[PDB]
Each structure stands twice: as C-alpha cells, then as structure tokens.
Length: 178
Ligand SMILES: [Zn+2]
Ligand SMILES: [Zn+2]
Ligand SMILES: [Zn+2]
Image 1 (cartoon, rainbow, N blue to C red):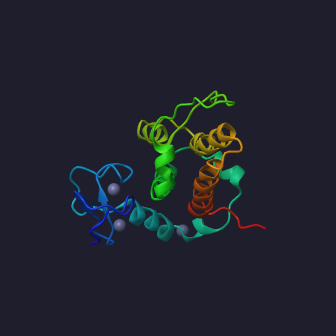
Image 2: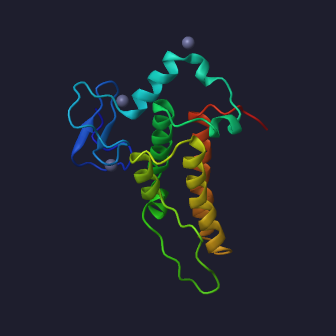
C-alpha cells in the first residue's frame, strides 16, 4: 500500500485499503474509516464495485434526472465520493472551514456554506435528494465568486468548482455534450 494519505498526500496514522493500494487518514476518508471490518475496502473500491455490478450505470444521464434521485445508499456513497474528490485538491483548504466576511466594498453571503458543513450534513443524513448536496456544493463557490468580486482570489472558486463539476459528471455519468 501507499505510504501517504490519498486525500491530503501526508504520512501519519494511515489505514490501508485491502482491495487497492490506497491509504487514508481516519477522517480524510469519507465516511471516516470504519472501526473494525477485515477486510476493508475504501470508497474508490466501493464505487468501482457499483459500476461493475451495473455496467449500464455508466451510460449517459441527464443532470435534471440525477438531481431528483433520492439519497438511497448508492447515491449517498456517490455524494460522499464526490465530496472526497474535492478534498483531494489542495485548494479545498480555502473552502473547508467556516468562512467570515469583512472586506471593504463587499457584503457577506446570505447563506454561508463550507465543505466541513457539507461533510457533517452527509454524515447526519440531512440530504433527501442528490439535489440538496449539489446545491450546497455549488453555493460554496458561488458565494466566493460574489464576495471576492474582481480580486484575483475569485479564481480559487473557479478552480475548485471546475474540480467539483468534472467529478460530478464522471461519478454520476452525466451525458457528454459540447
Ligand atoms: Zn489525509
Ligand atoms: Zn481501495
Ligand atoms: Zn445489470
């Protein structure tokens, strides 16, 4: 197995996947690495299994259909994985913890949002449909863009949003378009 966490790329107290060479810190994996379970399979392996059990799941889908899906166990897992893929980018540090807003010429957002709050919301099964999760994720970046206006820091929001959206299209097999 790898000697660094797949998500944060640091060594430390790592838990190793039994079905692929990835390793994780306990709270870097989503959901948090399970207490017992031998063998243990990580979220990458669990997602690959879903795909392999239902090859047709990789045919293209309409986003509108995906968003209306109820958060049954497979959709819950897919949102957990998509959240993890965003944490895998180092620029996610800007969006992880609760933000605050005091900048001359801007007003903070009406509904602040951040990745750790989404992580808790998923853990506590607060989303009933995929739409709930996706709206909160997208709000993170939209708030950032709106607040930082013309400061070049706005680009961090564009960059992390692009990582989100590419992984959303991949994980939920959204029909390719120009
Ligand atoms: Zn880690
Ligand atoms: Zn694995
Ligand atoms: Zn089948």
